[PDB]
Amino acid sequence: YKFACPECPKRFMRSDHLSKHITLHELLGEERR
Image (cartoon, rainbow, N blue to C red):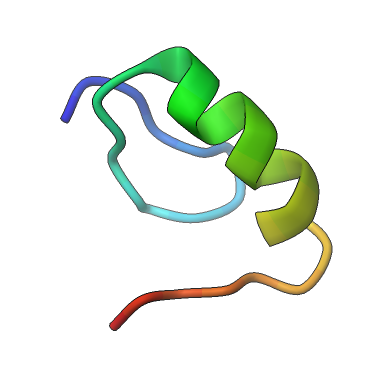
């Protein structure tokens, strides 16, 4: 953990881990759990 998407509360280890996930997660929002 270190970062945090502007849309979801998901905490990733690196900013890039989100940057790629945000563009898609901000669209629909695919959550693991």
